[PDB]
């Protein structure tokens, strides 16, 4: 409450004009942060803001409760849904901020180079919606591989992504085979193109 | 037959002269003229069927034909700066070529290091 008001002031002084940034980092938490975030951005503080949002997300949850919630994915309390809903809001904030960026690289690499498996999975999901999916191939993140794998069964794009993703011939081929065999309607011409591709990987 | 292989060898050689010493664009044109390497579609396989048939002299030469193609193809298709830019072709060409190379690596010296030039 009062602390929050102080935080707004903390940033506000920073709006007028390194230190205030640090002071904000200390304060960071919740919804008021949304308004506060716009303020951080004013003096081009995109990169720091993301870590900020992420750290906050982790700070509330510590830790890994949401992951359990997803596993069940139950509508019931399960592990508590509340943690999940809360983080997503923060995640949306991170994505929302990412969009505004469009010195682009420094901001993005920060997000990717962070250890958060719901975050990245969410990020990817965010990317697919954008049809950013091609960019996905590029992402190095160790989180990415499991993301593709789990999602693997407009998933076809994910798979077109996947076989392409696998530099390795063997892995790539196995996927296209499944691609061809798959139960979603895909023309035979493509089914064969998959095989032609898969066979080539022989 | 004897003369034909002769001309092919000469054509390949002129390709060499112009390969390096610049003239990236010219090299593709000539290589395609050879009618050895699949520029078109996935007809890469027909290039397989017609491969074993190839005379011993040419069968040997193909290694460099490939990789010359993926080179010019690479350098020419250096991602440009800032309109009609059909990057797609000279891209499809690499693809068909790679499928080709993929099909005959065993019947080749053993350098599918086309891959190194292929990517960046």
Image (spheres, rainbow, N blue to C red):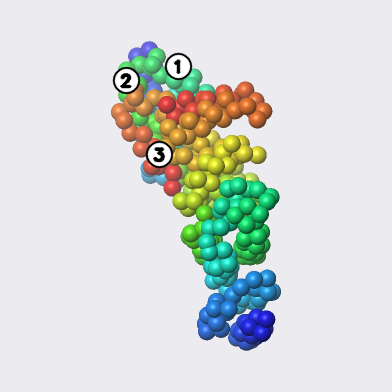
Residue A38 placement: quadrant: bottom right
Marks 3/2 same chain: yes
Mark 3 Cα-neighbour bin, 10 Å: few <14, some 14–19, many ≥20: few
Q: CA distance from mark 3 to mark 1?
A: 23 Å
Residue A45 visible: yes
Which of pointers 3 and 1 lies earlier in the amino acid sequence? 1
**Image vertical order of residue A42 relative to residue B20, above or below:** below
Q: Position of residue A62 (x, y in %)?
A: 53, 64
Disc 1: which residue: B49
Q: CA distance from mark 2 to mark 1?
A: 17 Å
Badge 2 sits on which subunit? Answer: B
Q: Of all residues shown, which one is farthest toward the left?
A: B109
Disc 3: which residue: B115
Q: Residue at x 33, y 33 (%)?
A: B111
Question: Are the residues flagged by discs 3 and 1 in contact, CB closer than 8 Å?
Answer: no
Give A82 or A182, whichever is nearer the viewer.
A82
Which of discs 2 and 1 lies nearer the camera? The answer is 1
Q: Of all residues shown, which one is farthest toward the front?
A: A77
Q: CA distance from mark 3 to mark 2?
A: 25 Å
Q: Position of residue B6 (x, y in %)?
A: 35, 20
Marks 2/1 same chain: yes
Which of discs 3 and 2 lies nearer the camera? The answer is 3
Q: Position of residue A190 (x, y in %)?
A: 60, 27
Badge 3 sits on which subunit? Answer: B
Q: Split into 4 quadrants, where in the image is the N terminus of chain B?
A: top left
Question: Are the residues flagged by discs 2 and 1 in contact, CB closer than 8 Å?
Answer: no
**Image vertical order of residue B35 relative to residue A162, above or below:** above
- Secondary structure under badge 3? helix
Disc 2: which residue: B57
């Amino acid at each position: 409450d009062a602390i929050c008001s102080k935080a707004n002031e903390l940033l506000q002084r920073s709006r007028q004009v390194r230190e205030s940034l640090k002071e904000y980092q200390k304060i960071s938490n919740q919804v008021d942060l949304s308004n506060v975030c716009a303020q951080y951005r004013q003096v081009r503080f995109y990169e720091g803001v993301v870590e900020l949002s992420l750290t906050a997300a982790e700070k509330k949850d510590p830790q890994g409760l949401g992951l359990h919630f997803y596993k069940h994915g139950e509508p019931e309390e399960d592990v508590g849904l509340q943690a999940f809903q809360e983080r997503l809001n923060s995640y949306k904030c991170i994505t929302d901020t990412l969009q505004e960026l469009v010195e682009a690289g420094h901001h993005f690499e920060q997000m990717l180079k962070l250890s958060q498996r719901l975050f990245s999975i969410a990020l990817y999901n965010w990317l697919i919606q954008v049809d950013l999916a091609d960019k996905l191939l590029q992402v190095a993140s160790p989180f990415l591989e499991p993301h593709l794998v789990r999602m693997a069964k407009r998933y076809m794009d994910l798979l077109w992504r996947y076989y392409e993703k696998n530099r390795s011939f063997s892995n790539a081929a196995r996927v296209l085979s499944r691609l061809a065999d798959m139960h979603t309607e895909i023309s035979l011409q493509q089914r064969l193109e998959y095989i032609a591709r898969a066979i080539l990987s022989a | 037959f004897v003369d034909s292989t002769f001309y092919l060898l000469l054509d390949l050689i002129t390709f060499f002269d112009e390969y390096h010493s610049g003239h990236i664009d010219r090299a593709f044109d000539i290589i395609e003229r050879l009618k050895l390497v699949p520029l078109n579609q996935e007809s890469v396989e027909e290039r397989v069927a017609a491969f074993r048939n190839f005379s011993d002299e040419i069968r040997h030469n193909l290694s460099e034909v490939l990789l010359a193609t993926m080179n010019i193809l690479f350098t020419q298709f250096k991602r440009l700066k800032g309109i009609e830019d059909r990057d797609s072709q000279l891209r499809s060409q690499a693809r068909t070529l790679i499928t080709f190379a993929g099909m005959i690596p065993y019947r080749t010296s053993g350098d599918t290091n086309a891959r190194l030039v292929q990517m960046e």
